[PDB]
Length: 466
Ligand SMILES: *[B@](*)(*)[C][N]C(=O)C1=C(O[C])[C]=[C][C]=C1O[C]
Ligand SMILES: [Mg+2]
Ligand SMILES: [Mg+2]
Image (tube, rainbow, N blue to C red; front, side):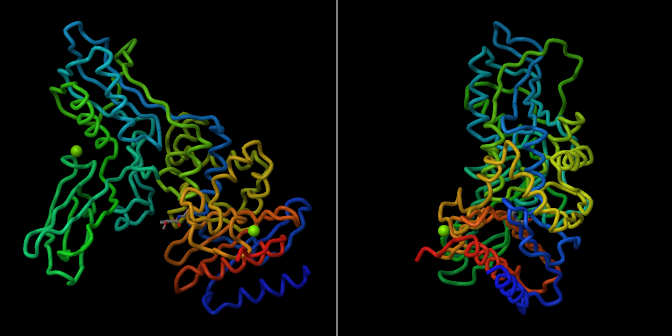
């Protein structure tokens, strides 16, 4: 039954949801290298979040499994016996997992080293990366949303999920007629506020909108939230992440008993300082452990940052240009043919990326025998698993099918794009697969993708847990 499997995929692909759509599909046995199936394998397509497959691959190469990202605090000289220090610098180096308690535990160290007073200004130094925040062809109307958060070297991640450059916004109703309450989260007194929202009557029209008007740093809230409505929480992106990190640090410094007499802003370590005094540091977890919340959940902010820290290592420049050449190179050096690949970001958000499916499977093949093979696969969403940090974006897909708990694969989906590629490990040889499609008019053909993935898990020697 190998001819018979082809019959099946051929049929699953005649689906009426793939109308006008160029789908590209490859399936490869790892152990025997035999090509199980190939349809439009060398066609050039937009890979959405599948691009992260390449990014994460090059990130383990250029940076290693053992790489950590540093964050430090700097004055000109040690703190006065009086207590006094001048201008102080919160300086990040591309930690994609920097938290609020992490900031606070840095603010401890500044107090716990003899600082009682900053008489000067507080500066945020995200100069490890350049200040180009968004890729050329990202859509301005997407900017308000998490997947489109601005790129800095020094960005405060939010939550267990380490969503970068963002703020949680809570909107609670009051009584009907009164305007709604609006919590700006971290960005309280950093981000501007326009609150035109209102509490509507009990059980009425919920028409609440949250948006950050393009090219401002105002969170703007409109519409009605009914009085009996369960409180609304929303992640929004703020302008200049690093400056918010500076603000959250001013706040951290104050509660940790350190006065700041000046302002918060952006600015670099003057370089006209000789033996600059580092009075607080912080190391992030290793890359292997950061791969988890990144790949599992498909973190965009993370990928770009990694690209930029790749350009750092190889070239000494957190540039998108620099990094992407670095991503290109690492891949080449890993044995993968980068002919059909066009690189434009690390997250695959941009519609100016291109991958062939043959290339995906190529990379899946290769990464399957690198030293970091085991950390790389640990991070890929596992099909049908309830546990968010395991299921990832495959938590509520393929449950109770041959696929469940078997298929590690990365999703990706945009208007007009979708991909699902990864491994199907079984008794009948390790399996690598790629499913990438564009052109479809309806919803992302997840039913079609799932169907292919499951049938492979069956072929590999698997059965549904019912
Ligand atoms: B890696 C999975 N990510 C995505 O599919 C994705 C979004 O999540 C819903 C949003 C925007 C882009 C995107 O992938 C490119
Ligand atoms: Mg605040
Ligand atoms: Mg099974």
